Image (tube, coloured by chain):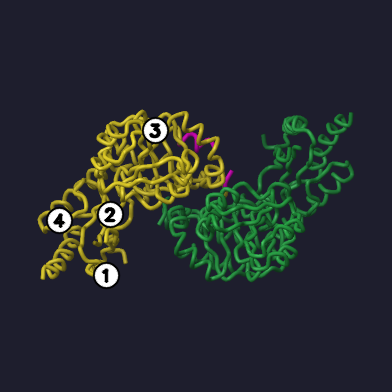
Chain colours: A yellow, B green
Amino acid sequence: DDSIIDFTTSDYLNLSSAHNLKHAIVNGFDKYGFGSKTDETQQFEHEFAKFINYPRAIFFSSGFMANLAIYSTLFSKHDSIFADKYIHASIIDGIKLSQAKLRRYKHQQLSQLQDIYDGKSFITTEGVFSTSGSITQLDKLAKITPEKLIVDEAHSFGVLGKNGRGAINSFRISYKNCLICVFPLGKAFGGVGAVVCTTEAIAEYLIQFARNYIYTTALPPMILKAALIQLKNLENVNDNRARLQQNITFFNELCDAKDLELVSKDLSPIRSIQLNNANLAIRLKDKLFENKIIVSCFRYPTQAILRFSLHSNNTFDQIQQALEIISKEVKYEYI
Amino acid sequence: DDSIIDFTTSDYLNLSSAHNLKHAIVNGFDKYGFGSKTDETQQFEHEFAKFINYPRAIFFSSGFMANLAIYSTLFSKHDSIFADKYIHASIIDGIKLSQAKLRRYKHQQLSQLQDIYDGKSFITTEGVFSTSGSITQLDKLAKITPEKLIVDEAHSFGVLGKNGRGAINSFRISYKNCLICVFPLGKAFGGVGAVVCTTEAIAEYLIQFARNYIYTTALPPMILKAALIQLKNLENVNDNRARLQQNITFFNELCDAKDLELVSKDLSPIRSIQLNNANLAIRLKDKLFENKIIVSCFRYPTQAILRFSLHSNNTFDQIQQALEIISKEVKYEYI
């Protein structure tokens, strides 16, 4: 019941239960009521852009709505966009609705991207990939596709970079290389919505041609006071980031020691364990869950993945117990 | 400052300031915090479907997200959809992203629809049109396009029908004639999100193929407790509906008496006054606003419209003052 070991939320900093947001919500609701239609939106956008160090920030109601706004208003069927084979399905949806032609490369194979790249099209990527937990080398990517980067920070924001400013920040990339980065606030930020950071040109262009996408879908204003506080919470919990890292490092050393294969050995809070058999994977999941341990399960290339989401409040005993149980079952498959 | 006469909100029942929602919000926030990822969602969907008398209800984060989910998953470029020339731009956006071919008819010209209709395609319409405030005769429409209706209830819900159940309800149309009706909760309901009411078949089909649209964009669970209460508020404020009607009836009698032309004489809370000159219209708007009266302004066919949104707390003195000022200026144009 409460002795649940959750390795599937995305609350990487345990901020969703921040204890200093209740007044904010209460006040926001007294001022704006329950509905819609802001001082605080612009205030938030100002503070976000400042934190990330971009010229402009537009607040959207969801990650998906941001992406749609971006791909459907800036691209058409005459453009191409290059994208990692494992890019998140939400981003693909946005792109496909735009009608742009998608061109794919194998996971993190920057060299292969180099081989097919056309010298002109935009490239979309994730700072940390939801699928494999790999960390894209934005600095190498910017050499290959200068001026042409779109980066989703769903899983880097709050986790990578200085004070959790994210992947763009941690690789020291400027809006001259990445014109548009998207910050969904549903994960480490422990909130809702998404912020698009861009140039003045792109922002104004988006505000004029994506008006319906921004305003017909806006979140209720009563929660923007809370969001300002959570931006500071995220900035402030460096000790939570350190805890998180310790769990990540332990996880990886334990998989190495038990010869459990990871899709990626990068230092991110998504750890995806590779199983050659789907059936074994549904088993392990049911097994772990009888032990009050909840993970996620996926199958893609022909292979199946048990996917762990780590968080700052997880312990090594929890991670040890889970991998012990996995390791034990994989040993029977060595037959 | 507070002596503002607003004729542009969509809070037709003045429910956005319902005094009995504060505990709901507070509790919802204690239970779910600020973020996402429900008992209450299904509870709400159950109660909504019951109120409207449909088999199923799916809760979406916005009207727009509902429409996109509908048009992009149930249609392709091989279908056509028939739609009133003034259908709301948000619905057109959804359709165009679906890639379905749009076929238009002149405003409320059911006979013209009959003349171009193909005997098979879906037709999309609004219960009350945001543009002109006309009330579509759903009962005549169902004779022309049996089984093929999609109806947006943005502006009918809470306002038309028994206890404010809406346009489908008030014309006694069954889900055999209208398979899908969409209820945006941002207007009279004074909340946020949208509910799609359909058949079991369509619902399940939507839940399986529009998963990303429903779950990657969901509202925070902390506000679903409040929504359940507001469903009852909306049901309960029959006296607000009567007040509203009195304002609507007064508005129309005063325009008749001053020979001010309405795009539509139907009994809805959107009243659109027809001006043959755009310039006069920006003037009137600035004029009304110096008098602490706020209306909305639009231009479409080659004509310009001053658009009044009435609400249950508006008075006849306010409506009289506003039309007096309009009437006075239009008299100079008779030169």
Indicate the quadrant containing the N terminus of chain B: top left, top right, bottom left or bottom right. top right
Q: Residue placed at 45% from the left, 36% from the top?
A: A44
- Chain letter belonging to callout 2: A
Spatial distance from mark 4 to mark 3, Cα to Cα?
Answer: 38 Å
Amino acid beneath label 1:
Asp
Residue on which the image places disc 3 = A179
- Chain letter belonging to callout 4: A
- Which disc number belongs to residue A255? 4
Residue on which the image places disc 2 = A309
Amino acid beneath label 2:
Ser
Spatial distance from mark 1 to mark 3, Cα to Cα?
Answer: 44 Å
- Which disc number belongs to residue A266? none
N-term mark: 4 or 3: 3
Task: Identify which residue, B260 or A298, lies in the foreground.
Answer: A298
- Label 4, secondary structure: give it: helix
x and y percent of residue B65 in the render? 52, 53
Spatial distance from mark 4 to mark 1, Cα to Cα?
Answer: 20 Å
Magenta region: A36-44
x and y percent of residue A232 in the render? 37, 38
- Chain letter belonging to callout 1: A
